[PDB]
Image (cartoon, rainbow over all chains, first blue to last red; front, side, top):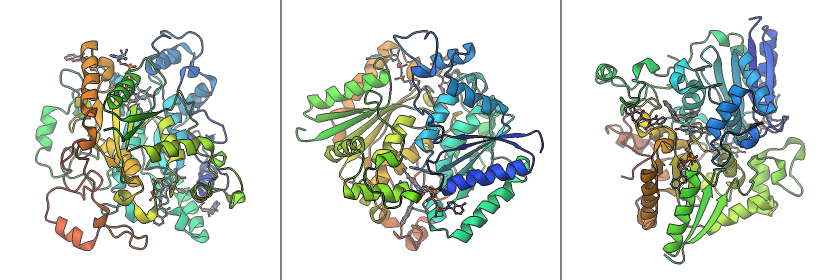
Length: 273
Length: 273
Ligand SMILES: Cc1cc2nc3c(=O)[nH]c(=O)nc-3n(C[C@H](O)[C@H](O)[C@H](O)COP(=O)(O)OP(=O)(O)OC[C@H]3O[C@@H](n4cnc5c(N)ncnc54)[C@H](O)[C@@H]3O)c2cc1C
Ligand SMILES: Cc1cc2nc3c(=O)[nH]c(=O)nc-3n(C[C@H](O)[C@H](O)[C@H](O)COP(=O)(O)OP(=O)(O)OC[C@H]3O[C@@H](n4cnc5c(N)ncnc54)[C@H](O)[C@@H]3O)c2cc1C
Ligand SMILES: O=C1Oc2ccccc2C(=O)[C@@H]1C[C@H]1C(=O)Oc2ccccc2C1=O
Ligand SMILES: O=C1Oc2ccccc2C(=O)[C@@H]1C[C@H]1C(=O)Oc2ccccc2C1=O
Ligand SMILES: O=C1Oc2ccccc2C(=O)[C@@H]1C[C@H]1C(=O)Oc2ccccc2C1=O
């Protein structure tokens, strides 16, 4: 695994946190196997998470009607993005594997990490309308979420009061990671870390290092391939008619988001096929 | 409707935006019906969206191992939260109706709005473990999302390339809003707003104002009531045995998150029953 490069994006303010220890465990395990490891500790960086015209240097094209998508895309093509954004984009370009380490907050990513996606995943660089999802710019990379929660796993089971964790993960793993082309690996889910004692926390750290010894060879999560859809406005970007006809008598839909009104395949966003 | 109060939280930097126009339309229509209207224009406020120990003044309980949940709950009880947080909490306490107006960004809320939830929805003030979801502190209030998207409506249909919008809405409407006790009203979904001509946009604003004339009398979205679950940590907050047995022979699950491996009832997060 010499020659492969990893990026660990951490979103936690405290160096005493378990999230920080998971970042250190990941970095140590990957380096031991020959990886180059680069980090984005967003809190330690004082990372600015708010998109604004200060993400762009030089001339704005239409300052009287500011449109962040058009202006940032033009800035990317012309080399006029803010230097802190350019630095993060270079880390992404270099990385084969991207690990996102964060506590679950309000059933999603921390605001500082959401803003990192918004400022760094600029159009053309991270996605194109003509090549969404599996054809996206990051299709040669793999991404993985490593999440800690306060709530127990049972709260996020099919019968738990919070509802299916697979639904919670969908907008992040499909809408952010896979939209840009990433193959998304099984998330590392560390449930109710606040009710886990010290020696058990050590084994959680060791298990994560163990998994990282062969993470590049894992099967990724299943998303419906874009070849199943008519990618044009005359068809409305809907699934092809012959695909709908083939699926019409299967009991399960294709994924969490493409459940088709049927049963969601079990752990679609948690376990590979 | 004189006597009732609304809070409009806007997450868009541009006064020239359609989001700002929707905020202005909402304020004018409610005021014309006698509502008191307060605003949290997060960009114009320069709102700080990043949780940290600077959200808390005075003596921390354990500064050597800072844990935001325990420290912020204690700070709320002792009156040691940062003044900008306190002011937003007072806005929430006064409001009967809360409108969230924002463009969809990476299939969720903008980072500045995500951080508003993180800094303002403090434990004990906005939620308690002993009274989750429909017993929560905001159970006398109603909330509504007013979202604009770049993508078209068909892209978010069951057969569309992005998948079911009901799945994308679930973590925000059930997890952020309903967990605190809000009754959640049908979201105002404005699709492909960058490809909607001017004639149509004007009518969208008039329709939004029309809806707001009787917004308080609408039926809210359906979430499984907390009485269906055993509400204690030891029991994992799992659905009651008798309830599981009774739902076993039903063809549809109860909601997006409580789909129970069965068909999701149509537009559970988009249309009231
Ligand atoms: C705004 C906010 C929103 C939240 N929303 C949700 C939600 O929606 N759903 C949900 O389930 N939870 C939610 N939570 C809870 C959150 O997910 C947990 O608090 C978080 O995952 C805890 O992870 P941590 O790194 O902070 O652990 P910490 O509390 O910092 O540490 C946990 C334990 O691990 C110890 N530890 C540290 N380093 C090591 C080491 N090398 N080796 C062994 N042990 C170590 C620590 O000393 C500590 O005892 C929220 C929390 C906040 C602040
Ligand atoms: C980081 C980022 C991430 C994004 N992620 C997603 C995603 O995941 N999925 C998705 O579908 N989209 C996504 N988008 C697109 C985003 O949702 C749309 O760009 C946004 O909703 C557009 O709303 P707006 O208010 O900015 O519209 P504007 O472009 O500001 O306005 C649209 C038209 O309405 C006009 N208008 C303004 N005021 C009025 C008025 N009083 N009366 C009549 N017309 C008026 C405006 O002049 C303009 O011509 C993303 C955008 C960004 C920047
Ligand atoms: O489930 C949750 O959802 C949240 C959503 C928004 C903000 C914070 C939280 C939490 O703290 C966690 C975990 C939370 C915890 O950490 O400890 C508990 C102890 C007893 C009963 C229940 C729990 C929990 O669910
Ligand atoms: O309205 C339309 O309907 C069509 C019917 C048949 C053939 C072509 C088209 C179009 O190009 C689009 C324009 C189209 C639209 O209206 O929605 C969008 C939403 C997001 C991004 C881009 C667009 C468009 O270009
Ligand atoms: O504006 C657009 O341009 C297009 C042109 C041709 C075909 C499809 C599209 C789109 O999907 C939309 C919206 C587009 C979308 O649907 O999802 C996103 C997710 C992340 C970031 C940005 C966006 C968008 O703007």
